[PDB]
Image (tube, coloured by chain):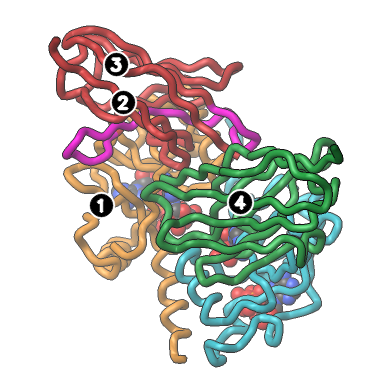
Chain colours: A green, B red, C orange, D cyan
Amino acid sequence: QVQLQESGGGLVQPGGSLRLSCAASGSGFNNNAMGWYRQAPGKQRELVAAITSFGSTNYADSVKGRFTISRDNAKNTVYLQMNSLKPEDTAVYYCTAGWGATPRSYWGQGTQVTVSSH
Amino acid sequence: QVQLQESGGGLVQPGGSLRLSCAASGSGFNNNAMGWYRQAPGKQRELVAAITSFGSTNYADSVKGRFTISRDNAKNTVYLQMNSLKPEDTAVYYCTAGWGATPRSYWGQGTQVTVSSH
Amino acid sequence: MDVMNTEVVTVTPEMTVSEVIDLILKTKHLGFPVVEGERLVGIITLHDIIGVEPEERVGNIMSREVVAVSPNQSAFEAFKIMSEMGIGRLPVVEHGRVVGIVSRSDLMRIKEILEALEV
Amino acid sequence: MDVMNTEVVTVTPEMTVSEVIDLILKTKHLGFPVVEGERLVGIITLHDIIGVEPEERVGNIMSREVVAVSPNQSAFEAFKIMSEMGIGRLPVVEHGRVVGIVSRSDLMRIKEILEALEV
Ligand SMILES: Nc1ncnc2c1ncn2[C@@H]1O[C@H](COP(=O)(O)OP(=O)(O)OP(=O)(O)O)[C@@H](O)[C@H]1O
Ligand SMILES: Nc1ncnc2c1ncn2[C@@H]1O[C@H](COP(=O)(O)OP(=O)(O)OP(=O)(O)O)[C@@H](O)[C@H]1O
Ligand SMILES: Nc1ncnc2c1ncn2[C@@H]1O[C@H](COP(=O)(O)O)[C@@H](O)[C@H]1O
Ligand SMILES: Nc1ncnc2c1ncn2[C@@H]1O[C@H](COP(=O)(O)O)[C@@H](O)[C@H]1O
């Protein structure tokens, strides 16, 4: 009914910019709210940014201004634009689907985003 | 929270036997009921066989006796053993997770099983 | 049927009430349609479960004459059936196969939602 | 908290009541905790929505003093808070972040389940 395929991520120098995308497929998906959760090595899962079908966004305090979220309704895909990437942004970034400002009903498999100095 | 990775399938001569497997990962999974749905080219989605965490099975009338379902609780994976494969068993076989005798909460991506005469 | 839950928690006639008790604990649902595959055969609620031995099978205490409804019928037609017979949950069947479920609560909420709709 | 729904339908203070109406239609929920990210700021139910213009923002009519509960507290402690103050739904917060939700109904059902447990 609902599938979430994440794309993008990987290495990015500190302070650089990187973008993530998540495609929503399936017949159980009908203009749901999509968002991005992450989880750092030792830390617990945490909301990064979400956006409803209306276009109403919701960011954590921690990536506010740096990260901006957008979605393509016809393609049913969401985009997380990450800028000014601090090393504390290194985590596995999971894509979620659901309803409201904190969608957690359906999850992706997570894509690794590493922010390290070369 | 819940991920379902299907394995197996493909070509099989009419009357032959083939097996499918589905691995359940994620922290939202906790001894859920797992089952198999399918969908033929023109037809609609249809239950094949399901099994609860207790081990209680539930088969459709159509694959009853031919198909038998089993699961591995420690590996959290289910097994659909298909025997005496008629050509009407050619369909995309989806793995599902949920509660009860007809779990439909979480779905897999589907694996193609083709029963054709060479 | 504008109102129905298509993710249905069902049971088989060979499951035991000890296992049905787990489903009430896990899903917090009052009743469950009994199915053979996807085909409705009976229904079992908490009324019919208390109190029998945990090894008792569903098919011996379930109600065989199930009042159901079709997906081609309006949600208001089910609200009439639920009130005319004082019945809690109504399975939704198509070709004798369970496709959803709608119950009183599900329709009582629609009343309150319709009350507040003058913008 | 043995009883709580961790998949929480929340709203932001900048969403409009026209969008909250859609959530009630989609999710059939009576109230929604208002969050900034994951941090609780307010709560809004159907009481506070009817009847204002659809362009009105949540943050202007939501209740700011939210009676919540922590996941380290028992479900029975929430049942006391719900009864002592006559409050429908109680958000569950940890470090000021919404992690679940429990409401009356959710606990009224536990009473009926506990009634039938003598096997
Ligand atoms: N939809 C239904 N169709 C047919 N029989 C039902 C249905 N729902 C319940 N029953 C049977 O009727 C009896 C009614 O008792 P129960 O409390 O279990 O359901 P109910 O009467 O709908 O609940 P309530 O009394 O809260 O309305 C049950 O024993 C059950 O076997
Ligand atoms: N958990 C809560 N914490 C703080 N304020 C709340 C809470 N729930 C509701 N409110 C506020 O109190 C008012 C009560 O009216 P409403 O019907 O919306 O909720 P309720 O009183 O819990 O519902 P009911 O009357 O069915 O119990 C609402 O306007 C809402 O803003
Ligand atoms: N057996 C079931 N399987 C799936 N959903 C159900 C079942 N019974 C009830 N529901 C839904 O869950 C809600 C709560 O059910 P109840 O507690 O029986 O009123 C209702 O609105 C129903 O739509
Ligand atoms: N805003 C919400 N988000 C997610 N779940 C909720 C919300 N409000 C209530 N619930 C749950 O859904 C059920 C129905 O809620 P209500 O209709 O408000 O009684 C309750 O048992 C709650 O546990």
Q: Are marks 4 and 3 in contact (CB under 8 Å)?
A: no
Comparing A81 with B48, the one in front is A81
The magenta stretch is B24-46
The mark found on residue B112 in the picture is: 2
Amino acid at dot 3: Phe
- Amino acid at dot 4: Arg
- Residue assigned mark 4: A104
* Amino acid type indicated by mark 2: Gln
Chain ID for label 1? C
If the picture is divided into quarters, which one holds ligand 4? Answer: bottom right
Mark 4–mark 2 CB contact (< 8 Å): no
Please tell me whether residue B28 belongs to the stretch shown in magenta.
Answer: yes
**Tag 1: residue type?**
Ala
Quarter of the image for the N terminus of chain C: give it: bottom left
Q: Residues within 10 Å of mark 3 (few under 14, many from 20)?
A: many
- At x 53%, y 41%, the residue is C24
Return the x and y of residue B21 as percentages of the image width and height. Answer: 43, 18
Q: Position of residue B63 (x, y in %)?
A: 23, 21
